[PDB]
Amino acid sequence: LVTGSEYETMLTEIMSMGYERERVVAALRASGNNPHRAVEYLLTGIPG
Image (cartoon, rainbow, N blue to C red):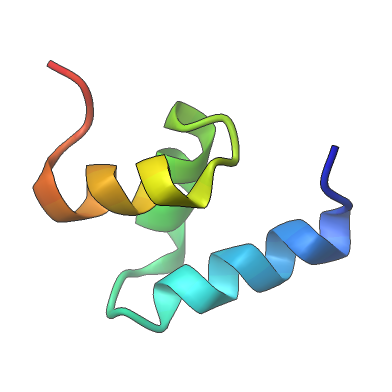
């Protein structure tokens, strides 16, 4: 289980690719905090 501070740095690190906070938050929820899947969803779409 990542800590809350590790979540915030994960979130900010992905935001550095040019995504707004609320989209990254939604992608990390959809990925269960796996950053690889979150970035996949931001690049090429959520499942479905």
